Image (cartoon, rainbow, N blue to C red; front, side, top):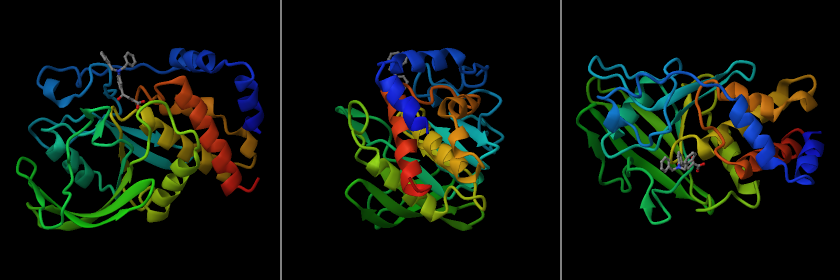
Length: 283
Ligand SMILES: O=C(O)C(=O)CC(=O)c1cccc(N(Cc2ccccc2)Cc2ccccc2)c1
């Protein structure tokens, strides 16, 4: 099993070597729209841009920009929208995308503040008595219920389109225990988190693409999607041992850059898949 390859690389400390080879092999496409002047204040980092060909477009005649990408995995029959953590003035855009893409869940893999810095705006209401209104995009957001477990929190939210007045239930899966530095020592919690997300139906076909984000929506985000797809693939392929992470990862990077930003992240990704493989597809 890929577990062997894992141990091989480990026994060679060749992770940075493997990871670098991928960074080199990765796809590179234009981001002309993201780089436009008007969309300047709509981006978080200078080096985290969505390719033009796979960027999600807002349905507003004004400016249709938002730093988010549609990662479509054909064989796995899965889709994910990776985006950057919302900025003070892109929260309305964020939720508009959620609404227009008919998403069911939003996955947050970061904490509002990490290392004494803000990593994104408080884009969802913390108290049910105090809803949130995004005047620019005319959407109302209401906290229905929160469930704080030891490693993550899950929230039910009501999103209403003030224009039409239709209402939708959005699940917010927030992974709150990812460490400030490095990656988890054990993939255990991360996997239960993934499974809870699946169990909700947010990744399922009868719904729009789940919306995933982190700090740049590429570091931990990529890991979340890479692990999901790989497991799903070992789940349907006649030959599970034929699922190649390195291969799946590059397919994914054809839709958004920066998935897996470090070698430890990669190693960790391998771990997650391997362990998850056992727990799911038997040993
Ligand atoms: O948790 C994760 O995995 C992340 O994904 C974390 C992250 O939010 C994220 C994203 C983009 C960039 C960065 N910098 C910050 C910087 C950039 C430009 C100028 C000054 C500072 C690091 C850097 C990386 C690669 C090349 C060059 C720099 C962090």
